[PDB]
Image: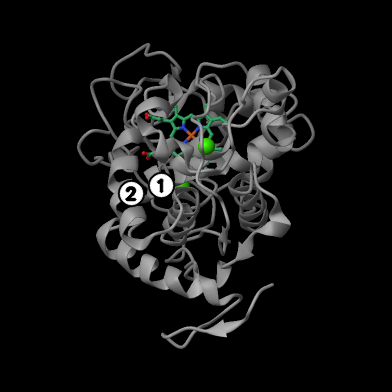
Amino acid sequence: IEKRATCSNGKTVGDASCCAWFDVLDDIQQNLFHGGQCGAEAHESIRLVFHDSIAISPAMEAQGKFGGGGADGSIMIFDDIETAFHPNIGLDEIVKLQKPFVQKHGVTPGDFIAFAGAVALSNCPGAPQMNFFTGRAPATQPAPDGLVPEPFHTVDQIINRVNDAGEFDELELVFMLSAHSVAAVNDVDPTVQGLPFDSTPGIFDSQFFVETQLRGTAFPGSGGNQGEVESPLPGEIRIQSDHTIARDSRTACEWQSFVNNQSKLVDDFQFIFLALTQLGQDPNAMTDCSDVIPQSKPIPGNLPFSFFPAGKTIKDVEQACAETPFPTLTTLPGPETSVQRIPPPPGA
Ligand code: HEM
Ligand SMILES: [Ca+2]
Ligand SMILES: [Ca+2]
């Protein structure tokens, strides 16, 4: 039973219970995201949503074991346990920055993680208009390990894991990897933190899908780290799983479909992000508080939506989609330039 209501700030929302999230919004925009930025804390918050949510397994439950609660705030509640798992490396820092907000505002940890993830995305130009539903009860048990994918897992292992967790198919796997468009890597190369996956880590766009399809020619920092392969630009990192998903015959044409197609990118990610945040939950038992999330902003300027970074042309693309040739994009002018690092807070 939802009660449409006008909050104290004058805005109308779907249920009166949503109004209290406007105070949470104001607090995290100022004190967690430094004035609404799509910087390191926003990226970490988006990563935390996946690591809290994908830890659920119908297959383990069928074996008599607890397979995890899905989107239940378990990675925050039992952080001493889940953040020690190898796939969750580096997440205790963002969990520690978020905890005080959960305590101050009296919301569940699962609902806060889903909220901060959606607000973080709304700070990145180009993001979809994000949803936010409430209702996740506090987890009562930590998830098991072995449920969050690693960059060195094969494509078959990853496809099978997301299919078990939420009945997601191989095309939906590609949809959710769009989040690597606003993201950096702090713990794979031990000599440098903050290496972005694409040349625009503050913009939700398809440069991740363009740049992962170019030929990898060098390591940005040290060579041969586990789960890392060569990348095409100085300062950019590329992980093994993204590299192989982009070239596998099952997923390569879906990976290429986002290039120069902003509306598909936004619509597909909007859809799959909402689905991840409902894992382990009953959708009809949740409350829609999407009207609290800020409107996303357009990408500023007048460059084409997708482009080759300076120094790269169609000859540097490793075409993997047999149905449709990679689109001929324009190249930015000038010499190749390094992607700038995104320094993380201490402890990342
Ligand atoms: C399906 C398989 C995936 C694998 C193997 C994977 C792998 C990784 C790795 C290795 C990192 C760097 C972690 C670190 O250095 O501590 C990373 C970062 C990131 N991942 Fe994924 N990822 C996956 C899917 C996703 C999904 C579905 C999302 C959606 C939210 C996501 C969002 C992020 C974000 C936003 C970052 C950047 C973190 C930051 O800047 O601090 N990833 N991913
Ligand atoms: Ca969880
Ligand atoms: Ca980007």
Residue 29 x, y percent position in the rendering: 33, 63
Q: Say which label, 2 or 1, has the lower sequence index.
A: 1
Residue 290: name its quadrant.
bottom right
Q: Residue furthest right?
A: 323
At horizontal 47% and vertical 23% (from top left) the residue drawn is: 216
Residue 8 x, y percent position in the rendering: 42, 86
Is residue 198 among the parts visible in the rendering?
yes
Q: Residues within 10 Å of mark 2 (few under 14, many from 20)?
A: many
Q: Does the beta carbon at disc 2 come under 8 Å from ligand 1?
A: no
From the image, which quarter does the C terminus lie in?
top left
Residue 11 x, y percent position in the rendering: 49, 84
**Residue type, mark 1 in image:** Ser
Pick whichever, 226 or 104, lies toward us.
104
Pick whichever, 135 or 168, lies toward us.
135
Q: Residues within 10 Å of mark 1 (few under 14, many from 20)?
A: many
Is 332 displayed left or right of 215 in the figure?
left
Q: Which residue is mark 1?
A: 45
**Residue type, mark 2 in image:** Gln
Q: Which residue is mark 2?
A: 98
